């Protein structure tokens, strides 16, 4: 969750 | 230096395709069983809306689009009369992989399929006018590693006059902070808002975005992010305000 696409 | 005309009010449309909910992809595409919802993406859509409204564009948002829906939207704009506009912008906020972006259904849209809808033959009312695409997505699953450095009538081509701003070089990830927005879009908007009033052109601004994003890091994975513009622009592109 805290990070990319 | 030759400069694109940029005086119409509105300047043009700025489409924003803002993909958040990937429940369909998780259900339907085996390899995307754990692809996450893109929490925080609205912060990017809002930044782009503020930024491009200040620059006199008419914003056209579309949320949570499958691939087929994206192509339908792009066809609508391909077929629109842009004769009274000076520019067209399309922003895509989604997951992606090498050369593609995902619809919310987990189908793939090659980036070429998106931009090629606006060539001069397909959209003559944009012929000779800048067409600008910003793509916020990963382009693969690799972390970009870091390296240590010291501290500081006439005819033109069908594919002329494009600018494609990618959040990342191919093969690599791009970052989204759910509480702030993406590294790339947030930097892009900050730079546009600061520098377009100074008269700076978009390639200069995108160089600054490269500089700023290159200083960010992911200290979980020791990851970096390297944005990458590509262009067939034939003139300087400025967005006066």
Image (spheres, coloured by chain):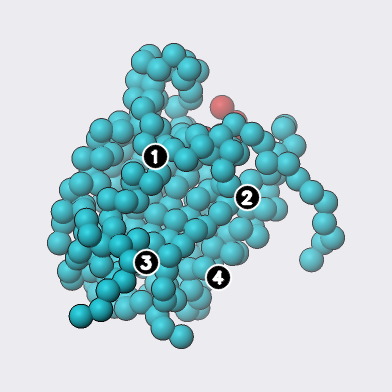
Q: Which residue is mark 2?
A: B226
- Asked which secondary structure carries label 4, the reply is helix
Query: Mark 3–mark 1 contact, CB under 8 Å?
Result: no
Label 4 environment density (alpha carbons within 10 Å; few <14, some 14–19, many ≥20) = some
Q: Are marks 3 and 1 on the same chain?
A: yes
Is disc 1 in the same subunit as disc 4? Answer: yes
Pointer 4: what residue? B204
Q: Relative to B179, is B209 above or below?
A: below
Q: Quadrant of residue B42?
A: top left
Whether residues under marks 3 and 4 lie with C-beta atoms below 8 angstroms apart, the answer is no
Q: Which residue is denoted by mark 1 in the rendering?
A: B110
Give a yes or no on whether discs 4 and 2 share a subunit: yes
Whether B142 is drawn above or below B213: the answer is above
Colour of the chain lettered B: cyan
User: Which chain letter matches label 3?
Assistant: B
Residue that appears at 31% across and 33% down = B67
Q: Are marks 1 and 2 on the same chain?
A: yes
Q: Quadrant of residue B102?
A: top left
Q: Which mark is residue B161?
A: 3
Give x and y (percent) for residue B24. Answer: 35, 20
């Amino acid at each position: 969750x805290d990070x990319x696409x | 230096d030759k400069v694109y005309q940029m005086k119409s009010k509105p300047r043009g449309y700025c489409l924003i395709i803002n993909n958040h909910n990937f429940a369909k992809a998780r259900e339907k595409v085996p390899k995307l069983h754990s692809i996450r919802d893109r929490n925080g993406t609205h912060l990017d859509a809002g930044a782009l809306t503020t930024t491009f409204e200040e620059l006199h564009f008419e914003i056209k948002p579309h949320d949570d689009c499958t691939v087929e829906q994206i192509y339908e939207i792009l066809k609508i704009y391909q077929l629109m009369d842009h004769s009274n506009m000076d520019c067209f912008i399309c922003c895509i906020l989604s997951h992606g992989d090498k050369g593609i972006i995902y619809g919310t259904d987990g189908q793939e849209a090659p980036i070429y399929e998106l931009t090629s809808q606006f060539t001069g033959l397909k959209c003559p009312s944009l012929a000779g006018k800048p067409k600008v695409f910003f793509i916020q997505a990963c382009q693969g699953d690799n972390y970009q590693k870091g390296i240590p450095v010291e501290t500081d009538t006439r005819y033109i081509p069908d594919e002329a006059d494009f600018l494609l701003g990618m959040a990342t070089v191919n093969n690599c990830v791009s970052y989204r902070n759910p509480a702030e927005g993406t590294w790339y879009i947030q930097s892009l908007c900050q730079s546009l808002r600061e520098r377009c009033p100074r008269g700076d052109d978009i390639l200069t601004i995108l160089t600054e975005v490269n500089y700023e994003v290159s200083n960010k890091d992911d200290k979980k994975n020791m990851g970096k992010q390297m944005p990458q513009p590509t262009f067939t622009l034939r003139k300087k592109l400025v967005f006066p305000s």
